[PDB]
Image: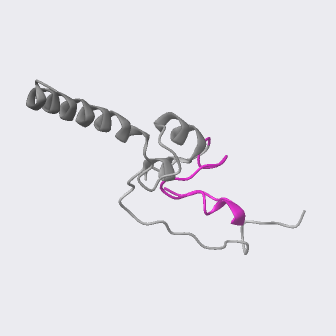
Amino acid sequence: DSFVIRGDEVRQIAPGQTGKIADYNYKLPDDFTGCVIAWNSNNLDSKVG
Amino acid sequence: SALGKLQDVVNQNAQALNTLVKQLSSNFGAISSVLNDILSRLDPPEAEV
């Protein structure tokens, strides 16, 4: 799965979390046997204005 | 104190039952002893713990 969120909302993409992006947009299961990968993409995902 | 042994057995059974009932009011290291209160005051992970 691939999506683009902000910095202060990366901690919500984890098993057993709460908020607005982890409860209304995209929620992970309790176990979620896998791995979370994220990195900054300000080089090409933010234009002037 | 005519029926001593029978009364002692009855009292032991009553005390065992009362202790087994009262054991539901101990925290055992938790914040409380009410499952509903725990589920309403804690997040899913801490509530599960």
Residue toward you, A45 or B22: B22
- Residue A39 left/right relative to B18: right
The x, y position of residue A7, in whole percent, is 70, 66
Q: Is residue B36 in view from this perspective?
A: yes
Specify the quadrant of the image occupied by residue A31: bottom left
Image position of A10 with respect to B46: above or below: below
Give the residue furthest to the top.
B2
Q: Is residue A29 in view from this perspective?
A: no
Q: Is residue B31 magenta?
A: no
The x, y position of residue B30, in whole percent, is 47, 52
Give the residue furthest to the front.
B1
- Residue B22 left/right relative to B6: right
- Residue A17 left/right relative to B21: right
Indicate the colouring scheme. one colour
The quadrant in which the C terminus of chain A is found is: bottom right
Specify the quadrant of the image occupied by residue B41: top right
- Residue A33 left/right relative to B16: right
Question: What residue is shown at x 61% (from left), y 44% (from top)?
Answer: A25
The x, y position of residue A29, in whole percent, is 43, 48
The x, y position of residue B8, in whole percent, is 16, 33
Q: Which residues are magenta?
A: A1-24
Image position of B17 with respect to A1: above or below: above
Image position of A49 with respect to B46: above or below: below
For the stretch drawn in magenta, the main secondary structure is: loop
Question: What residue is shown at x 49% (from left), y 47% (from top)?
Answer: B47
Q: Is residue A8 magenta?
A: yes
